[PDB]
Image (cartoon, rainbow, N blue to C red; front, top):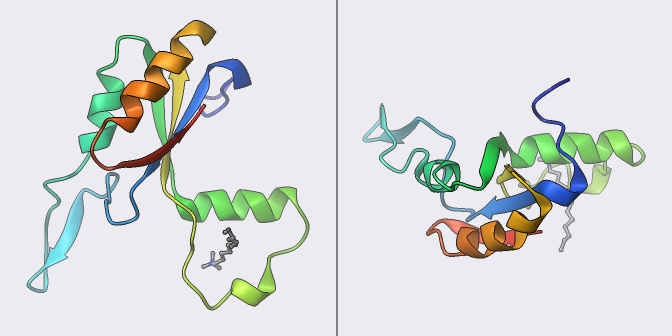
Amino acid sequence: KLATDIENNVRVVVYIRKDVEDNSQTIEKEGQTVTNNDYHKVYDSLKNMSTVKSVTFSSKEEQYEKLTEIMGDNWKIFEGDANPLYDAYIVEANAPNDVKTIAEDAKKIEGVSEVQD
Ligand SMILES: CCCCCCCCCCCC[N+](C)(C)C
């Protein structure tokens, strides 16, 4: 059994604003590698909810690889361009009934772009 395998009825997906790097520990400033003060701001608010069991980062890169894996071949015409997908956290609720509450509080976290239940 693996951690990234969560049942449909208890999964909430939390999409991160495209200009927030919640999973990046360091960023570039003045040519140096320095602390990202916004690191895990969204992660921690989700992890602090009493009804959530796990929160796992899913990058936009990873989401596109899996899409090409599940559907046919890569989507060649977009290969030169930026990835338009959103980084996301995959949140596991403690019970199905907690999902609607989790998704509502999640949209109120600053940095959260959208939440899918
Ligand atoms: C409105 C929704 C339409 C969006 C469809 C876009 C498909 C994403 C392809 C990204 C490939 C870029 N690449 C190679 C760097 C990962």
